[PDB]
Image (cartoon, protein in one colour):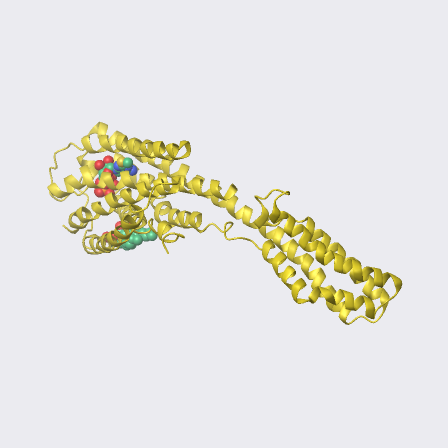
Length: 389
Ligand SMILES: CSc1nc(N)c2ncn([C@@H]3O[C@H](COP(=O)(O)OP(=O)(O)OP(=O)(O)O)[C@@H](O)[C@H]3O)c2n1
């Protein structure tokens, strides 16, 4: 009512920071639209990112109206409170909702029209839901601005309008946390799968060590008993690695040629150990060592290089796209939603002190800037792809 807010810093710092976002964002979205609208909608991920790029556009279009209003209350600030600021929040939760759907879609592809119709109807669901939340926030901004200095939208809203403001901010907390928990669960399952794929590849490489290091002992061996002990250990290690299922041959049947090449590949190496085993059983040292050294030949070394390469962890396991989403959530959306509820409470009722209401506003405005940073960082999911370079 009689509270004074220090605008000496916010009128220089924030319009300058938002000029940078408006500049970068238009270049980023300019490149994103000419790349995404020139390609067809053959997958669900393309449809969701085609909707995210048009939502990012409306978010960037809001910034010039904020640059002028924060720099200077008047008819411009009244309009910002009524139209542009509401549009910013509308497209923000649209971007969050689609980011959650992109995380689910990309997670389902790591585990493996009617499929495309589902993605298209879910797009309509998000756009209609957020508009039905934003529309009353625009209409109910009806209260005469008595003073030309009091720059707060809560003071320009009616009794029912202030109630709808409190409801929407709670619904938006539910919208954020449902999408944020979706991104956490998906990421955890991917990271858990990466550990499971690592252990299986580590056990495969350990069998190769109890085949390479044991062969070095045979080269320095003197008695027939020392060669016979190492030959039995090498045969067991090669047999154990043959039974193993690598992460590359995960979605492959045991009757497939790819699975058969891996099984027979080890049998060629097992055979050479078995040939030297017959010589070692009799009591031969030089005759058994010559047959054991046949595993180091140009042809057999290629087989060892092939079987090791098949065992290796693929790039399909390392999901960079889901990690970009979780990083965007922690930097852009998490700090903002951790300061919205204490700020919304100071807006609904004049219960806080002048210094208390001011401190909450500066924290809200600073965190709101990081939320705006997502609009210039969201098309990077498209830029870090195979068909984008
Ligand atoms: C999906 S539509 C939506 N979602 C919100 N979370 C949301 N939060 C606030 N709004 C609406 O956006 C308008 C201004 O938001 P605001 O953050 O309360 O204004 P402000 O940052 O200038 O804070 P004050 O100076 O008003 O205290 C206002 O009409 C309000 O009803 C919102 N609209």
